[PDB]
Image (tube, rainbow over all chains, first blue to last red; front, side, top):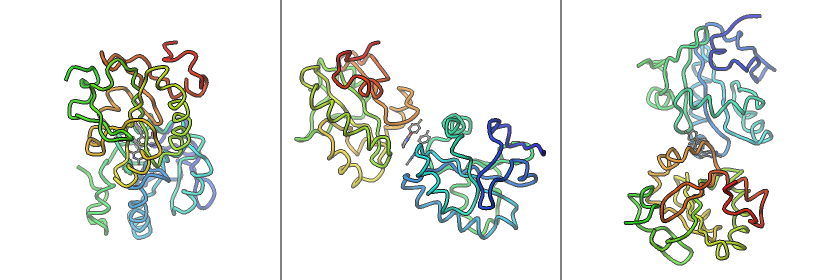
Length: 146
Length: 145
Ligand SMILES: Cc1nc2scc(-c3ccc(F)cc3)c2c(=O)[nH]1
Ligand SMILES: Cc1nc2scc(-c3ccc(F)cc3)c2c(=O)[nH]1
């Protein structure tokens, strides 16, 4: 077992959904993590997700980060379909009861929203990456601290 | 103007209806449900037709009105969605006020109904979305509990 600073905000979470199966929070040691508050049916999310996917494909290795979907979907089949087409990780559907309070904790007032977190400490690096990705597509100023 | 709905909607004048606009004053003496919703939200899309049935049966006899408060940002979605509904709507040009209205009543998800006395603006319930399911004949309307 390995600890994780993400457990500061996901104390009920252990595994994340991934394209390789499941990954522990501990597996993200040393990384920058983006919590991506989104939903399958939200129109502005539909416009943003491909932009974030392109950024992810380009930079996630060289800039040592992961993206974890935090979905507002309340329908499990919709959740899996939506996440299936993304390239990154997801908080499992069985954590859906925590999503509202997690949004409140980070001052999420609408979606899409990105919250940038240090995986080791749980420190919030930034809250504006949803726009910075568009402003800075090659991530010159990543991870966009204030 | 004088109605207690005006305390919540200071930038509004009129609400949309099926036959053109109506004043806030036209709701004098009514129980009013503020219906926090969005055209693309699945539980809303499932609840709207249920609420429509409830409205059609009871709105006259139990002297209430429903007012759509929509999270829609796309005007074509708004008009189409409100087109499914028999009741009133906060006009699309007031949509910038929807979030603060949600915060006024502690709306933390949708669909949500907030029940208000129109004249005084008093909140008389927050659980009507649930009560409509359990009590579709409105025996316990307006559900003080
Ligand atoms: C399209 C859309 N869907 C959703 S699902 C949840 C939200 C949302 C709204 C307000 C908040 F304070 C937090 C999330 C939200 C939103 O803002 N827009
Ligand atoms: C489907 C859906 N859409 C929307 S659009 C806005 C909301 C929402 C979310 C959180 C709040 F505090 C208020 C509204 C919301 C929601 O909760 N569910």
